[PDB]
Image (cartoon, rainbow, N blue to C red; front, top):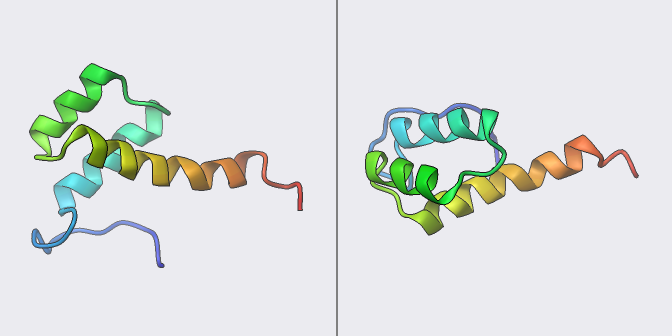
Length: 71
């Protein structure tokens, strides 16, 4: 896949807004808390699992960046 920004559509798994707010709060917090995740779910019409899974995917690649110069 080709990571980066992504906006418009409003008709697939995530919108502009959904994708924007997500890369926002994965910048500062490495892990959303219970309340933060629930809050973001209300705004973004997502659910705590969907938010967890997006954030988990973003967080995984970071592990092979941060310390992954072991190959």
